[PDB]
Amino acid sequence: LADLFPGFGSEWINTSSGRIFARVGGDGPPLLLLHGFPQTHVMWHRVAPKLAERFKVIVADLPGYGWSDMPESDEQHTPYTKRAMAKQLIEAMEQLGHVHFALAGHDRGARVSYRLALDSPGRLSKLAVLDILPTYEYWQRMNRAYALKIYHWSFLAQPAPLPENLLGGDPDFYVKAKLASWTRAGDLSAFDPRAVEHYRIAFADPMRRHVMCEDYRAGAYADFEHDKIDVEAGNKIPVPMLALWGASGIAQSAATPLDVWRKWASDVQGAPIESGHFLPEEAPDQTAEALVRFFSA
Amino acid sequence: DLADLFPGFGSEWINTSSGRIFARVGGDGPPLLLLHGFPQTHVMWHRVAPKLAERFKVIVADLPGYGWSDMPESDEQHTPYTKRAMAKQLIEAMEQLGHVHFALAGHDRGARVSYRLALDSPGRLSKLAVLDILPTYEYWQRMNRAYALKIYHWSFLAQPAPLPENLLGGDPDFYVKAKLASWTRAGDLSAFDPRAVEHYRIAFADPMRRHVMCEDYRAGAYADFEHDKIDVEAGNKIPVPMLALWGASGIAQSAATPLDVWRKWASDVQGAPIESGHFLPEEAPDQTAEALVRFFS
């Protein structure tokens, strides 16, 4: 597997729920980058160098993803709820001495991020979320059109071992299909093939696939419940936040992203980027510029 | 290999302009067509059809593309697997038997054919019974988080080929058994005759058959919904006396109280819950059979 972060260190961060793998590079204020599904921390490899010019950039595999340890799940999918993941990453950052940090997340990692910001806003200086709306909003917008677009939200949340069993016949196909289907071009051309091999290898592990289903199961249940509480309580993220979404990404299919994020966040700015879902790989320069600008003041 | 679950029924290959319809035919009296759904074949009627064959000419047909019926070539609109096309094809099949006015009971996909048949060609039907469905439009209209999770396969199987085909290919025996079990009251396969499960398993083992099923679901997400929408918007009601049966633990009762729903779609509908999951004729054969004989005779 290729090293896509030349000069970045490698950290195995112990937490109470398992080790968090991260690449660490740069200097300056700490910036935690969180990938999503079906990816690993390497999806940041095209923007993290630019960030590392200005920030101490920690590029972490989510709990259960990549090379992070996989906590055993339970009937409530607890370790794969974003609340739990957020607590675990808070612990990881504390192990590095980062109790107040900037956070950019993509996809599942963005869900961890905004849940972190709701649960533990004091930990964040600024938050960027890439190509998501809150989990509650996706579910609340789950009509025919969206159920077809993000069918995987309900498919991967089916009780084990149904998606696991189907995924296991040809894991390569599914990970490549999801990477391709959510890009602007509809193929794998936006990705570095070395990055794709990282994603594919991670997906080849039946336990990693199970974790991904657990993440989606949490996404269908506890994550939704946690968001529902906040949205019904009018809890808003108080951390200044950037919502970036791809013009051809997933978030803009459900709804206009800034309008939605303004319901969740008291201090949100937003920008579309001409890109499919995978902003940092499809549009690394625009993404990296957006993030540097936002986190730089 | 495959048991004959209709002793004393004939076996008829009915030619149509779109391919052969396989049917078991027994009994004498007014013709009654029984249509199975997914992921089953005509043999799902094996426990109720002999009771029906006491008073009716019972024709127990595999849906177009299912079971042993031929698989018409699909197209980009999934035309042959739209319920309107399957209804047309079954009307033609019944015409080959000289049945231009018949009773019709359908379960699951076959019930969708049946009510579409009733809407498109109500003169063809004396009486219609639909088992454990609401109209396709209603499922999509009701689409929300809860229904999305419950009937996730509506969106999963409707994904563009070859995504669901490849996934189903990962563990087809598991999938068909999981569907059967998960939609019963028991939650396992104990309501089924193992010889019937063998029929369903073998049908499901054929990739071409699985492709047809995905075509059926793709139709169900697109054209079938559009056809239904036209009828809702025109206020077109089914004028054929109809019986809506649903499993107290079935799919239909979740989304909305089925009689109340069907009364929007049909002018003369009676309904009854059956103490069963989705597979009324197999989980509750006596209760189902009685209800059908009472209604049809």
Image (cartoon, coloured by chain):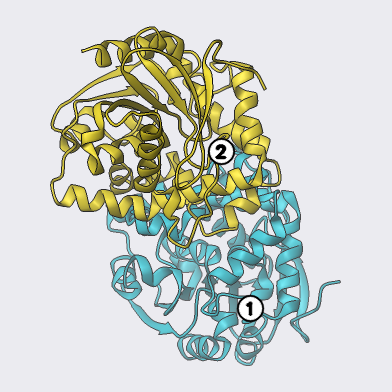
Chain colours: A yellow, B cyan
Mark 2: few/some/many CA within 10 Å (<14, 14-19, 20+): some
For residue A1, the mark is none
For residue B160, the mark is 2
Q: Is residue B208 left or right of residue A71?
A: right
Q: Is residue B3 left or right of residue B259?
A: right
For residue B45, the mark is 1
Residue A179: image x %, image y %?
Answer: 54, 28
Mark 1: few/some/many CA within 10 Å (<14, 14-19, 20+): many
Query: Measuring 58% from the left and 34% from the top, which residue is drawn there?
Result: A67
**Quadrant in which the C terminus of chain A is drawn:** top left
Judged from the image, the secondary structure of the residue bearing numbered disc 2 is: loop
Question: Which is in the foreground here, disc 1 or disc 2?
Answer: 2
From this view, report whether residue B104 is shown above or below residue A173.
below
Residues flagged by tags 1 and 2 on a common chain: yes
Residue A184: image x %, image y %?
Answer: 46, 20
Chain label for disc 1: B
Say which label, 1 or 2, has the lower sequence index.
1
The three-letter code of the residue at mark 1 reads Trp
Q: Are marks 1 and 2 in contact (CB under 8 Å)?
A: no
| Residue placed most toward the observer, B152 or B50 | B152
The three-letter code of the residue at mark 2 reads Pro
Query: Measuring 62% from the left and 47% from the top, which residue is drawn there?
Result: A207
**Quadrant in which the N terminus of chain A is drawn:** top right
From this view, report whether residue B159 is shown above or below residue A9.
below
Query: Measuring 58% from the left and 78% from the top, which residue is drawn there?
Result: B32
Q: Is residue B126 left or right of residue A264?
A: right
Mark 1 → mark 2, Cα distance in angstroms: 31 Å
| Residue placed most toward the observer, B267 or B180 | B180
From this view, report whether residue A219 is shown above or below residue A271.
below
**Which image quadrant for residue A250?**
top left
